[PDB]
C-alpha cells in the first residue's frame, strides 16, 4: 500500500475544469514536457498557480526529467633385404677395437644356439637375428661404433622395410649413405629393380642432400671372390646410382664379407681369397669422410626459425610418457639443451633436458651433458615439463619467437609421377609416407597436370618452363585434425613425401600449401 | 528382412504401401535406400511422460506416429537408423489417434516391430533390394583384421562395406638401446592378448564363414597363431571348431586399404565364398588396370561417361547407390539417359550398393565411371578438364 494513481480523469468532472485548455498554453510558453502538467494539476487539485510556479521552477535538474663439438658422422645402411646388410652392420658394431667383447660374443652365441648354427663373430650375430624375430627387432635402431677418425651412427634399413624410413625423414641425415649389394647372380639381379624399395631408399638420400655414398659388395664368398663378377657388378651398380643422381667417381666400392668379416675392419690382405684388390677397407672408407668444420661458434644453417618435426613419442623416467623422449629431425633452425620448445598443437611447452645429435651415443642414464645441433640433424630429445598426451608424431615444435608454427587437413602438393602400372585417377587412394607417419590419403581431384586437366600418367612433369608434373590436392582419410605438416619451403623433410599405390611407389612431391 | 505387405493401390499406379520388418543391420542399410524424404512412416513408440503443471500427471498407452519423413540419423556400425519428421497428424482421427498434433517426432528402428512405408518413388532398383537382398539365405560371410607393425583394425566386410568395429592398438616396439628392454616383448604379449579378447567378443562362429588375417610382414601369421593359442587356453570351441574359416593374406599397407588388396586381387579370394562379392570385384579390378595403364579405356566423371556414350564405346557402365540415395531425385533422370545413350553407342551396367568399399571407390569417382570397348584418347578436351 503505496501510490495513489487514481484521480486520473474521474476528478476532472468531479471538480469541473474540463482540461483541454491550460495544455497548449503553458507547454509552448514554457518548453518542457507533458505528464508533469497532469500530475501537478491533480497534486494541487485543479489550482492553476502553484502548479505553474512549480512549472517555472521545473526544468532545474537540467534534463527534462662458443664451443664446437666435432662429429661423429652418421650413416644409413641401405640394401635390398637379403644381402645380409644386418650381418655386415652388426660386424661394424661388434666392439669398436675389437674382440674383448668376450661377454657379447658369448651372448650372441647363446642367442639360439651355442651348439646349433655355429659361430665366427657374425654367424652368431645372425642367430641374434633369429631370436630377435620372436619379438620383431630386439636391438635398437640406436647403434653406434667408433673408428680411428670418427664416431659413427648407424641406422640399418631392415629386415622387413622400416628403418629406411628411420634414416631420411628419419634421423640425422646421412653424411654418407651405404648401399649393400649381394654379389650373387639372383640376388644382385633382384634388389636392384627400378621398382625396388632399394632404389627408393637410395633416391631419398640423393634428393635429401646426401652427397657421399660408399658401395659395399657383400657375399663375395659365394661368387668365389671373383674379379670378373666384381667389375661386372661395379658396372651395373653405378649406372643405376647415376639414374638415382649419384656421382660414380665419388663413390667408393669396397669388396666385403659381413659373414667372414673380410675387408670390414682390416684391408683385404686379410682376405687371401682376393689377391688382386689393393685398396682400403669398409671402416677405412667410412672414416674417409671429410670433417666439416664445426661452427662459426655460435652460428647458422638455421638461425632461421626453429622447426622440429616429431618422428616418435615414447615414455621415459625423467622425461614423461611423452614430453618424455621425442625423436625427429631439425627441419630448420637449431635447438640446444635447457631451452624451451613450444608445441602449437597441444598449446603446451617443455624444457629440453637433453639432446642427442646424429650418431647415436651418450645414453640418457650415463651423462646428461652434450653440445649442440644445426638443421638437417636428427635429434632425440628429452622434454622435462610436459605430459604424455601433449605431443603426438606429426607435430612440429618451435620457439615462441616465430612461434606456433601453424597446422591442418588437406593440402596442395606438386607431385611428380614415375613409371606406373596404375596411374592416379582423381579420387584414388594412396599411402603417403612423410616421416614416421604412413597414412592413407585420397588424391581427390587432380587440379592440374602438365597444365591441363587430365588423369595422371607416367613420367609426367611439365616438359619445360614451369614444372607441372601434377598439381594435386591430397586429403587424409584417417583422422580429424588429420596431420601436422609444413610446406617444403620453410622446411623440406616435413614437406617432402612419397606416394605409393599398393606396393609400388607412384610419385613424390612437395607440399605447396596448407588448407583447412 | 521380412515383408508383411506390399501393395499396389488402384488410384496410384506408382509408389506403394510397404509393411516390413528389418532383421539385422544389413536390413537397416536396405531400409536406408528405400525411405525418401516426404514418404510417411507409421510406428509404435512409448510417448509417455509429462510436466506438472496441472496434475502430476500422465497415463501411458502405446501411441503410434504417422510421421512425415524429413531426415535421418544413420550409423551402420552402431546398428542404428532413426527417421525424424513431423506428425502427419491423423488423418480423420483414423490414425495418429492419441497423438498430440504439433510436435516433431522421430522413429528409431527396432528388429522387433514392423512399420509401414507409404512410399512415393518406389522403384525397380529398390524392389530388387526388397525382393533379392532381402536375401533370406544370406551369402556375405566375412570379417577381417588388417594389422601394421603397431596398429590393428577389427573390421567386418559387409554386403557392401569395410566397416571398422575397433581401432585397437598397443605400445608397439620401437627398438630400444638395450637388447630390447623386455618392454618390447612384454608389450607385444599384451597386444596378442588384446586382439584375441576383442575378436572373441566381436566375432561369432555361427553366422560367419570367412575370417581374413592380412598384414605387411609376418604380423598376420603371428596373429593367427596368437588367436589360436589363446583359444586352446580358453578352450573356445566357437573358434577351434572353425580352424577352416581363417585365411591369412599379405597386403602392402596394414590400414583398411589391405582389405581391397586381398578381396579384389586374385591372390586369396577366387570363387570360394564369393556370391554377393562375385563380378563386382573383377570389374572394379579391370577398371583400374585399364585407366591406370594410361590406355584411355577406363573413364570416370559425368561428362566423359556421357561422351564415351556418344561413340557407343562403353563395355561396362559403372554407377553407385551412394550418389543415388545420397540425397536428390532429379539428377538420376540424366544418369538413366546416360546409360541408354552410351549403350545405344555401346554396353551392360553395374550398380554398386554403397556403404561398400567398391561403391565408395566409385563414390570417390563421383558415382559414375565406365570401361570401354576401344581407346578414346582425349575425352577430357572439347569438354574442358582432365
Image: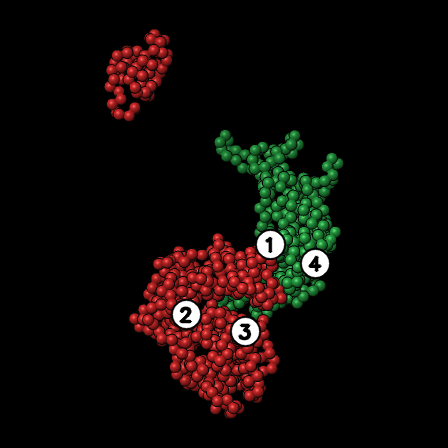
Chain colours: A red, B green
Mark toward the viewer: 3 or 2:
3
Please provide percent x and percent y for residue A419.
59, 68
Q: Residues within 10 Å of mark 1 (few under 14, many from 20)?
A: some
The residue under label 1 is B385
The residue under label 2 is A377
Which mark, by number, is residue B123? none
Mark toward the viewer: 3 or 4:
3
At a point 51% along the width and 68% down the height, the residue shown is B188
Q: Quadrant of residue A440?
A: bottom right
The residue under label 3 is A243
* Chain designation of label 3: A
At a point 47% along the width and 69% down the height, the residue shown is A208
In the rendered image, the vertical position of residue B232 relative to residue B275, given as above or below: below
Please provide percent x and percent y for residue B243.
65, 66
Left or right: residue A67 compared with residue B123: left
How far separated are the C-alphas under marks 2 and 1? Answer: 43 Å
Q: Quadrant of residue A379?
A: bottom left
Which mark, by number, is residue B372? 4
Q: Are marks 1 and 3 on the same chain?
A: no
Please provide percent x and percent y for residue B260.
62, 61
How far separated are the C-alphas under marks 1 and 3? Answer: 34 Å
Pointers 2 and 1 in contact (CB under 8 A)? no
Q: Looking at the image, is mark 3 or mark 2 earlier in the sequence?
A: 3
Q: Could you say which is closer to the camera, residue A79 or residue A95?
A: A79
In terms of secondary structure, where does tag 1 sit? loop
At a point 61% along the width and 33% down the height, the residue shown is B89
Mark toward the viewer: 4 or 1:
1
Amino acid at each position: 500500500g503505496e501510490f495513489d494513481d487514481y484521480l486520473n480523469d474521474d476528478e476532472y468532472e468531479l471538480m469541473n475544469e474540463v482540461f483541454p485548455t491550460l495544455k497548449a498554453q503553458l507547454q509552448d510558453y514554457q518548453g518542457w514536457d507533458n505528464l508533469s502538467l497532469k500530475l501537478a494539476l491533480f497534486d494541487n487539485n485543479f489550482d492553476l498557480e502553484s502548479t505553474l510556479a512549480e512549472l517555472k521552477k521545473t526544468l532545474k535538474k537540467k534534463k527534462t526529467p662458443v664451443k664446437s663439438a666435432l662429429p661423429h658422422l652418421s650413416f644409413v645402411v641401405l640394401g635390398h633385404v637379403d644381402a645380409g646388410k644386418s650381418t655386415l652392420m652388426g660386424r661394424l658394431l661388434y666392439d669398436l677395437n675389437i674382440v674383448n667383447q668376450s661377454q657379447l660374443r658369448k651372448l650372441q652365441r647363446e642367442s639360439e644356439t651355442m651348439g646349433k648354427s655355429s659361430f665366427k663373430f657374425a654367424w652368431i650375430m645372425d642367430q641374434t637375428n633369429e631370436e630377435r624375430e620372436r619379438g620383431v627387432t630386439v636391438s635398437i635402431c640406436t647403434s653406434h661404433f667408433s673408428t680411428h677418425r670418427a664416431n659413427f651412427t648407424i641406422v640399418d634399413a631392415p629386415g622387413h622395410r622400416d628403418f629406411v624410413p628411420n634414416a631420411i625423414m628419419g634421423i640425422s641425415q646421412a653424411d654418407m649413405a651405404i648401399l649393400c649389394v649381394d654379389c650373387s647372380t639372383n640376388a644382385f639381379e633382384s634388389g636392384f629393380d627400378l621398382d625396388g624399395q632399394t632404389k627408393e631408399h637410395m633416391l631419398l638420400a640423393s634428393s635429401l642432400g646426401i652427397h657421399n655414398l660408399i658401395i659395399a659388395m657383400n657375399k663375395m664368398d659365394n661368387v668365389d671372390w671373383s674379379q670378373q663378377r666384381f667389375e661386372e657388378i661395379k658396372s651395373k651398380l653405378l649406372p643405376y646410382l647415376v639414374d638415382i643422381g649419384f656421382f660414380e667417381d665419388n663413390i667408393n666400392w669396397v669388396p666385403i664379407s659381413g659373414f667372414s668379416g673380410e675387408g670390414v675392419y682390416k684391408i683385404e690382405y686379410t682376405d687371401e681369397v682376393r689377391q688382386w684388390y689393393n685398396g682400403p677397407n669398409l671402416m677405412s672408407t667410412l672414416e674417409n669422410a671429410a670433417f666439416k668444420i664445426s661452427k662459426e661458434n655460435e652460428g647458422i644453417n638455421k638461425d632461421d626459425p626453429f622447426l622440429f618435426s616429431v618422428l616418435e613419442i615414447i615414455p621415459s623416467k625423467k622425461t614423461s610418457n611423452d614430453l618424455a623422449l621425442v625423436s625427429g629431425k631439425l627441419e630448420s633452425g637449431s635447438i640446444q639443451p635447457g631451452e624451451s620448445l613450444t608445441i602449437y598443437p597441444s598449446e603446451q611447452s617443455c624444457i629440453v633436458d637433453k639432446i642427442q645429435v646424429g650418431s647415436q651415443q651418450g645414453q640418457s642414464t650415463n651423462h646428461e651433458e652434450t653440445d649442440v645441433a644445426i638443421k638437417g640433424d636428427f635429434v632425440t630429445l628429452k622434454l622435462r615439463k610436459a605430459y604424455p598426451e601433449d605431443i603426438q608424431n606429426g607435430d612440429l615444435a618451435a620457439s615462441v619467437d616465430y612461434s606456433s608454427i601453424h597446422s591442418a587437413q588437406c593440402f596442395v602438393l606438386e607431385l611428380t609421377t614415375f613409371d606406373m602400372n596404375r596411374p592416379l585417377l582423381p579420387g584414388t587412394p594412396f599411402i603417403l609416407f612423410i616421416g614416421v607417419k604412413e597414412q592413407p590419403a585420397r588424391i581427390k581431384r587432380l587440379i592440374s597436370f602438365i597444365d591441363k586437366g587430365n588423369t595422371a600418367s607416367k613420367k609426367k612433369i611439365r616438359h619445360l618452363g614451369s614444372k607441372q608434373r601434377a598439381f594435386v590436392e591430397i586429403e587424409l582419410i584417417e583422422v580429424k585434425r588429420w596431420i601436422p605438416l609444413l610446406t617444403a619451403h620453410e622446411n623440406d623433410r616435413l614437406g617432402r613425401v612419397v606416394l605409393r599405390k599398393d606396393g609400388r611407389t607412384i610419385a613424390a612431391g612437395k607440399i605447396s600449401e596448407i588448407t583447412q | 528382412m521380412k515383408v508383411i505387405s506390399l501393395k499396389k493401390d488402384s488410384f496410384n499406379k506408382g509408389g506403394a504401401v510397404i509393411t516390413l520388418l528389418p532383421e539385422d543391420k544389413e536390413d537397416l542399410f536396405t531400409v536406408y535406400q528405400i525411405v525418401d524424404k516426404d514418404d510417411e512412416l507409421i510406428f509404435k513408440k512409448k510417448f509417455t511422460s509429462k510436466l506438472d503443471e496441472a496434475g502430476k500427471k500422465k497415463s501411458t498407452d502405446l501411441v503410434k506416429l504417422k510421421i512425415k519423413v524429413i531426415s535421418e540419423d544413420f550409423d551402420m556400425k552402431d546398428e542404428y537408423l532413426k527417421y525424424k519428421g513431423v506428425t502427419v497428424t491423423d488423418e480423420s482421427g483414423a490414425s495418429n489417434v492419441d497423438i498430440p498434433v504439433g510436435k516433431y517426432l522421430s522413429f528409431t528402428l527396432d528388429y522387433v516391430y514392423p512399420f509401414t512405408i507409404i512410399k512415393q518413388n518406389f522403384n525397380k532398383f529398390m524392389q530388387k533390394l526388397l525382393n533379392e537382398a532381402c536375401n533370406i539365405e544370406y551369402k556375405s560371410d566375412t570379417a577381417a583384421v588388417v594389422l601394421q607393425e603397431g596398429i590393428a583394425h577389427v573390421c567386418l566386410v559387409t554386403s557392401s562395406s569395410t566397416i571398422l568395429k575397433q581401432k585397437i592398438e598397443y605400445s608397439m616396439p620401437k627398438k630400444k638401446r638395450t637388447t630390447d628392454v623386455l618392454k618390447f616383448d612384454e608389450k607385444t604379449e599384451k597386444f596378442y592378448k588384446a586382439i584375441y579378447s576383442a575378436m572373441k567378443k566381436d566375432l561369432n562362429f555361427d553366422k560367419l564363414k570367412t575370417i581374413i588375417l592380412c598384414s605387411p610382414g609376418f604380423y598376420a601369421k603371428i596373429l593367427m597363431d596368437k588367436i589360436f593359442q589363446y583359444a586352446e587356453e580358453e578352450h573356445n570351441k566357437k573358434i577351434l571348431d572353425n580352424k577352416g574359416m581363417f585365411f591369412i593374406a599379405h597386403c602392402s599397407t596394414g590400414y583398411l586399404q589391405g582389405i581391397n588388396e586381398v578381396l579384389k586381387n586374385p591372390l586369396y579370394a577366387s570363387k570360394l565364398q564369393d556370391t554377393k562379392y562375385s563380378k563386382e570385384i573383377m570389374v572394379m579390378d579391370e577398371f583400374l588396370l585399364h585407366l591406370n595403364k594410361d590406355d584411355d579405356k577406363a573413364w570416370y566423371g559425368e561428362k566423359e561417361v556421357v561422351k564415351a556414350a556418344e561413340y557407343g564405346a562403353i563395355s561396362y557402365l559403372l554407377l553407385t547407390d551412394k550418389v543415388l540415395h545420397s540425397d536428390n531425385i532429379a539428377q538420376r533422370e540424366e544418369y538413366l539417359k546416360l546409360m541408354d545413350s552410351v549403350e545405344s553407342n555401346g554396353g551392360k551396367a553395374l550398380v554398386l550398393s554403397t556403404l561398400h568399399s567398391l561403391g565408395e571407390e566409385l563414390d570417390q569417382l563421383t558415382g559414375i565411371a565406365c570401361i570401354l570397348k576401344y581407346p578414346l584418347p582425349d575425352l577430357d578436351e572439347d569438354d574442358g578438364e582432365e
